[PDB]
Length: 127
Image 1 (cartoon, rainbow, N blue to C red):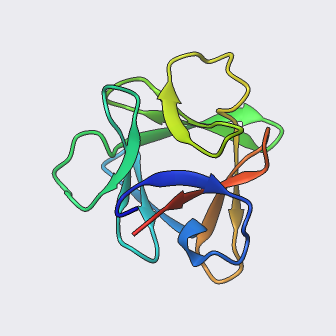
Image 2: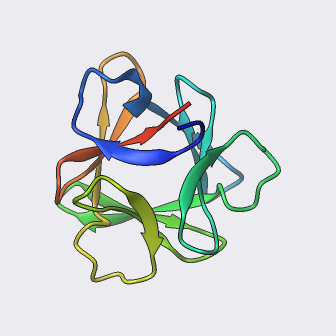
């Protein structure tokens, strides 16, 4: 519960809203609007949320994949964010994985949604 990250197709769930903020020059943080937690990919491939601003595993690089899709890559570990068909979220270094392509879209209220194209699931950080 507290601090877990998973995927959902529940578009009404406010926990799918994110803020993308610059971290230096070429990287971003992916912050849950509702809880203030940052997405983190741990060296072991697990993905969770943290409010530890000093954490080195919250920095991401967004790379264009064409067709309006992006990859979300953790700078520290080289792992791409993945949403699995079962709704779990983890990291993989396999660039050929079909579950690492995201669409970033405006929610309409100023926040953004992070949707995995393959499964149509949105990233969610739970409180």
